[PDB]
Amino acid sequence: MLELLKSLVFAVIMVPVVMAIILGLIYGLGEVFNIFS
Amino acid sequence: MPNFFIDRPIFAWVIAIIIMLAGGLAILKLPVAQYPTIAPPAVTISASYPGADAKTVQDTVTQVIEQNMNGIDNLMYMSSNSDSTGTVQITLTFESGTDADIAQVQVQNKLQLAMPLLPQEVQQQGVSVEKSSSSFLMVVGVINTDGTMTQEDISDYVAANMKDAISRTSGVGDVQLFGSQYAMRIWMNPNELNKFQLTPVDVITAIKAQNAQVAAGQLGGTPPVKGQQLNASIIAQTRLTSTEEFGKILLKVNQDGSRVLLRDVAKIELGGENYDIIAEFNGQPASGLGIKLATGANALDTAAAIRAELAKMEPFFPSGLKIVYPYDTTPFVKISIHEVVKTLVEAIILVFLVMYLFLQNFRATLIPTIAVPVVLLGTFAVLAAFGFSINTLTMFGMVLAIGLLVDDAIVVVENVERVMAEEGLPPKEATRKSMGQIQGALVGIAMVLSAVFVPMAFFGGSTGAIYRQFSITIVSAMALSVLVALILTPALCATMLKPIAKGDHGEGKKGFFGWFNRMFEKSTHHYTDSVGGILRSTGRYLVLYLIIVVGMAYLFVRLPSSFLPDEDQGVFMTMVQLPAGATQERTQKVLNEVTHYYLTKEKNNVESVFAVNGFGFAGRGQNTGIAFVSLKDWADRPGEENKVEAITMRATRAFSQIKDAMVFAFNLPAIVELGTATGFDFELIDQAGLGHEKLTQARNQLLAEAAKHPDMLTSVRPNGLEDTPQFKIDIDQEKAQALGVSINDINTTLGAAWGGSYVNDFIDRGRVKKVYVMSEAKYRMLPDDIGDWYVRAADGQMVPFSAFSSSRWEYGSPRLERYNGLPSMEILGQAAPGKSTGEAMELMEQLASKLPTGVGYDWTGMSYQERLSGNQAPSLYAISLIVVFLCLAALYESWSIPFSVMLVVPLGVIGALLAATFRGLTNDVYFQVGLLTTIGLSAKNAILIVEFAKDLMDKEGKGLIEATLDAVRMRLRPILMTSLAFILGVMPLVISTGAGSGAQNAVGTGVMGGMVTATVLAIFFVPVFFVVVRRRF
Amino acid sequence: GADAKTVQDTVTQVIEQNMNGIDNLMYMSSNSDSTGTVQITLTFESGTDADIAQVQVQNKLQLAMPLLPQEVQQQGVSVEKSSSSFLMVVGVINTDGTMT
């Protein structure tokens, strides 16, 4: 079962990214509303 | 109730145990089919009347049957088609849910009484009475690779040496043969008959005469003589077992006694009952077994058992004999399983990750991993308890139900960590308070969603059956979760969590986790920093809320609709049409050109060609035929070019170049019963019995205005068929019996000589089988061959036809329809792009309206249904709107605050649309059930926020905002937990290509993005909703 | 007036075929006899509905009637919920002998 080692990595590798996605959203978006406030 | 179990964790485990068993007890007993029943019960009658014409079939048989269908129940409508193959098919349409058997038995029994009224040859041939299933588990192709047999030759070994065994396999309900058994093919030569002054009748009666069952009696049978002691059974003439015997079937004998034999004036060999259809598999004679999945059988199980049966006949196969499986559903289903659990188990891991990334310790990150399976296991037992089957529909809904399952626990175990991290309280006591706060929250939610998900099960007809597979899947698995959330996880939250000191978000940790928490807690601040800012000035964020909402409809309505995504299935059909009466041989060449083309150009991806000559979808006979092609597995077909629809048009573009035919290849509707969402089925009905021609004229007339509104319509076409030159012949009655020549012999010789005639039964190899009598093809080809045939005058002289007979070509429609027992003509079309059907339908009605006197119409099929289940849509939304507001107001005791929740609805939905249109999608239920799990989770996060915020005002007394901020912050992480978990679990379904991909990708995109905006947007705006409702009130 | 074997291929096996794929079908046993007559007794799951059972059977059976030699059809073919054990037997006589 290289099946799980196959998904295991990516399933882990994305975790920071998508969290990195949205922290940047709130970074960029939190800039939207102060700017649009 | 949560505290009931806190004091009884084992009593929680105990229940948690039973669920795994029952659930487990379901995994074994839970049925398997790619799809469940959707199509409404329909009966189909099949009668054949050999060597005949549509109007005969109609006149003599159909309308008779049309009459006697009376008295049956739950009829939607009655369809009929008559044809020049001397065939009828009467399909009866019965209300969805109507017991199909009662439906069946009634029909067949209405038929019994009407059987007598039918022609004998109709009666002696029989009629076949069916529930309607065009589904097949798989197509068993069979072949002989040494070319040592015909398909008829092979046809028999199928029925005789194969067909029954598989019919006796476990899990198969239905066994079709795509070829005919041998029949005795008698081929009559007039030139021999006249030489002997003879007729087929002479042949006929003789055949009947000397092939039959002559029953006898007994020696010693009752009553005997007293003194008897030797009684047995008497054996006397019986049917013949072999051709050569049939030859000795003795046409006649003399006073001297010389024998005139059957073979002394007509060839004899066994043969196909119908030479109608030819088979070729990759260029050689063939036949096939339609195999259908038995009700509730395990689709993955039967196809194998089939493979096993056919594996053991292998030693018993003649040289060159071989099997093929040009079609099977099982392949696509197995993967569909393995793709679903891979979605569940890998999502349980992400959660284990996510909880780890946050809690960064092993124990709590275990608990949902306990909580998540139990419901899943538990769900299958709810499903299998009242007995749904694992199917394509039911699997997607489960994964779509993840998003509600994942977060239920996280929310639960979340709030306990906070109390601990903030209040440092032992998990057990900490657990209660978490429950104390949110318990009422869960209740309201689980009310809400069930108000959202239950609405759709009341949907009608075919589509509703689609919606209540998800709905009943999504309503139960969500229910069980709340029981768990309220029962096990808390006792898992009380017992299995370790204490942490007061004041610790973990900033003081070393390494990536201290760096982490510091970052997150900091990311928390700015957000609320603006949110509070967001809240100082609401008016702006109200204006901009309108903006988003507008684009919703704008992007919502701009988005077209469909039923189901189209998948590369490995197989596709290509359809031929020749001109009318255009012969079979011609039909067969382009096929080989068709077949060869694949194997020529498509050699890489195309494994096989299974060819059918003379059988169309649009009606049968020589000038049509289909090539059913198979491919190599997707993994053998890299890139989209190698994929069907890509293959399709490529193949199509080349067949455009063809002469003499309409050739087009197309994909197979994942459900061949669903038709088209933009298309419509319609009937041009003659209410007045005007006959045929006039009825036509309105039809084409109806296309005229139709084709004058492509702006609405498109592809508007009659489905049926056109009058052909067809050969009249006139009997001169008077000339005839002036020769002393009786009519039947004329009629009978005729229909039998040219038409071919089934006499009676014999047996072969112990197999009872048919007899036919007919003229050698070269004899029966042509009119000048009419007079080649002679008749015995009552005085004994042989009488040709050209004597009494007078003939002409003429036009007649070599197919006919009656709809609800009125002659019908079908039309077929679709709405123009950007146009919905009903707009088209409305126009037909208008254009139908303006037709000549006596002209009616009826919509039907997907139009008949699209009519009734349209009325139902809004009345449910309101019901679906009403129920939803009530419950929160119960939870909140507020006639306003619930509005603060209801405004979240466009926030998830909007993002959802973006992704479907940016990828350019269409509106389907994988999408429209996905539009739902999204909305709820967005109302999941606002209700809870407003729960605390409310909780802060009524209990801690804190004013509106300082609580509003207070709630949004505390719930920050879990939303982030939620969205973080859910999003990555569905990630594979976004990129997923391959088999089942279009469907997988369907749920994925509309869900992922809308869960981008719901996560991000709602958490900003929902505090305003609350504040703007609360202040206003 | 015929023989079992014929009867078996004329009808019985004509029958065995359409009988594939009816619900709760535990086993089949058929017979054909030199009296020219058949019995085919079906048995379905304990708890099965015999009428419903009667129906699916009745349904498939229709398929094979055209496959019948005529007199069988004319003789007719009945499907009946069966029990091979009589409830009872009531006997009769004439005790003054006045009858046979």
Image (cartoon, coloured by chain):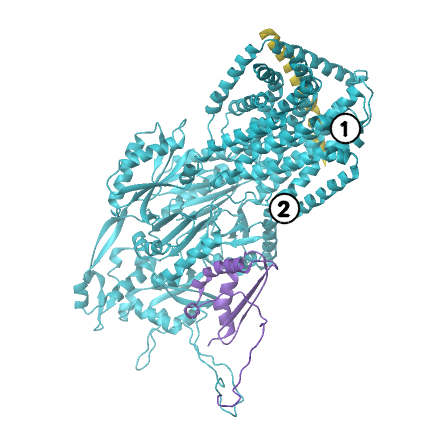
Relative to A7, is B1030 on the left or the right?
left
Relative to B98, is B205 on the left or the right?
left
- Whole-percent x, y for residue C6 in the image: 49, 71
Nearest to viewer (mark 2 / mark 1): 1
Q: Mark 2 highlights which residue?
A: B385
Q: CA distance from mark 2 to mark 1?
A: 33 Å
The answer to whether residue B216 is above or below residue B767 is below
Q: Amino acid at mark 1?
A: Thr
- Whole-percent x, y for residue B677 in the image: 44, 34
Within 10 Å of disc 2 (Cα), the crowding (few <14, some 14-19, many 20+) is: some
Say whether residue B354 is visible: no
Q: Amino acid at mark 2?
A: Ala
Q: The chain drawn purple is chain what?
A: C
Q: Secondary structure at mark 2?
A: helix
Say whether residue B342 is visible: yes
Which hue belongs to chain A?
Answer: yellow
What is the quadrant of residue B394 in the picture? Answer: top right
Q: Are marks 2 and 1 in contact (CB under 8 Å)?
A: no
Numbered disc 2: what chain?
Answer: B
